Image (cartoon, rainbow over all chains, first blue to last red; front, side, top):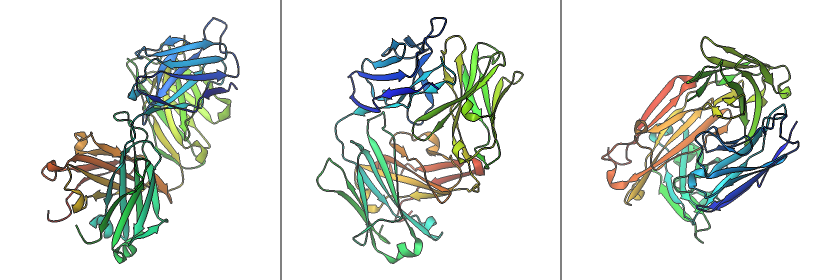
Length: 219
Length: 222
């Protein structure tokens, strides 16, 4: 089968600057009628892939003309003249010349922006959950940049490692930031046994963690 | 313009079959296009499964070795996917996609439907309000949230104030543990607006036909 190799794996670009990404196929994609069935697609976060380029070099229907496809034979390039935040996502190439049809492994475009510290919020378990037997403590670390971040949980001042599940958003095109949620789940009986709960976020924007805490049974 | 939409059961037992429908509107399925099925696995991995074209001719990936059938019903302007002998490796987001036969142009994909291959039982979520602690309400903005816990399979939908609150929202990918998922969402508003303007998280779990509309009440007197 034809192997479609994209490089780079990831690219981080400032709004207004150009971007260029490569797709190389293991076999030539020209056909017997002079057509090259090479498409480029973009997949934005939480969306389906959408058309960009087809026939190797042609703008697909409705696509902004900031996108250009070039190349021939086995080596293809997608260029974005000036990147906008809504261009972030994963770019794929696809070939339709050789059965079975195959896709590149994707190149993820990240928007580079100024560092931002996270906005940290901690939430006690709800009264409803506490009637259940379980207890979840939730901490949101929102709208930060760059994406790498660390969260540490403490119960009465001591660090707690098990029962922690984290989830990260994709980059947001509205402000080019990332967000993260961390949930500490305990039994209700263990939660009701201890007093103070603390979420600590460590990010490159500051040498000192952002700490948010509460006491059980205080508003 | 042409619009595509996948439908079909979101949870399939191992060794049974997935059966999906693609409804095409805005274009006749007997003209011009190849009607494709494509699926997506974790890791940006896309796999072309096959097509049926405008004349009814089909093609499918040898990777699917005899397990796949692609068919159509021209009276309903629909085409279909059946994939048999499924295993957990067939868990994926399934897409239908039309491309023009002549040049591969005009690619139009449905929204995608998740199919989970699992023996685990369908379970409705509990939806818990995340009300801010008192000490974090005295700023100019305030963050509230909702925790959707203990459901199976994916997906759920979550909106705030029936969708009329869409700015300042973060809805996080679900996390799976012991065959149940948990998902959270935060919303941030100008603090002086709350609690005068109420905030409700609306959760739907189609697989269990369950909806919850949870109003966030402040901690403290209500």
